[PDB]
Image (cartoon, rainbow over all chains, first blue to last red; front, side, top):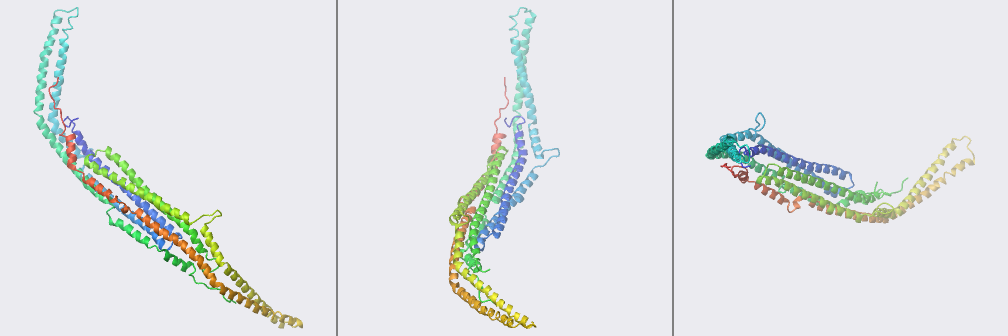
Length: 288
Length: 288
């Protein structure tokens, strides 16, 4: 599972397709939060429109009605703010990532991204010679082991050729030859297996240099997405932060003033003059 | 049309039933806003839960992953905030109004509010005498025209007499009886009519005093609800304003701090040592 194993570089190459996937994930994440902002804003607008009508058609008038009516304005202003959050999330943030994704990942007409194919081809090139050599080394490995294995089998051949009745002179003096055949045969493949081994060893330095070369390029492409993510995220934080927006605090300073403008006395003074004792009256008199 | 007309004090009595209804309107208004605040919170909670899972299972790791995850924590903090707005609107404001409504208005077994029935009884009792005197004046009025018109019924007959060729003897004088007596009651009813009028005009002062006494009582009761509405709306105002929450700004300070912690280089070093050239490798050797 080590990077240096043949083909294990694929994990690094995979990170490229993953990088494109992560940009799409972030985009969906933000799109989803934007819908949530719009939803809260829309429910507030609906609530404001519904209650503006109910208060207006209801029996509450005067300065107290204005105090109550101020809450519909508050909801409408909080809604505008969340619609701005949504607008900033989609028009700026979402679009910025959508465009970066497009400028960094290019489809190769055949499927997949050109940057992935590039990385893959660079790693192959850099691994090709070493892989070829490692290949012959393995062959020389299964060879030496094939010899050793075929040795003891012959060593026990003439051995188990004693507890047998029909033990001809040749049929027994010849089976002892196979042992000698395998004897040097093993030492033979041995040197073979040893040659390729040290040949591989002397070829690893170059091999590692080429692999680290390609890996570094990948690290550089990845660094771009990572820095880009931090940059956009700092911008998303700003768009969501309503705690440092004066316009938000203004909503409530204004709401408070409207409420404080409620004047019980003045309201009742009007009622007296327009619906109570304060009303003029045409008292009865002689009428013929 | 005027407050002083018999029975027109009803509009003042109605304000009482309306006062109770307005308390319920306010409650529903707050209740409706509370559901909206909870809904936004519910959506934030879900968005956070969903993305935490998608981010953790996805291919983004290191400090950049932590920066992204900071947004799930923000949605959670904001959710708790809005859940609390709902809690304050319902546990404090809604309840406060509900308790005020139960202490200010008392439903009676026979139906209707005690304080509405009191107002009605109070006005009736303050208007009873004057109303009775008015009817008297009304009777003297219609009884005056009855004779005032009864005379011109016989007086006209005087003409229907001259037109009578027969010119009946005493039957002519007989008509001269319904002309003197009829014009006789005209002076009687007149004096009566003017007498009852003078009487009404005499009791009018006490009438106004009695009505204004009951009216002032209705004004003071209404004042209680108007002042209460102002007091509670200021509390609602404070419960809606998230700027009033000490840690509101900390949510965004923490989010920003977590994002700033994103370190492309650090993340890249990790990948190399754990997934790249930095990994250990058991280079091939002589095996047997």
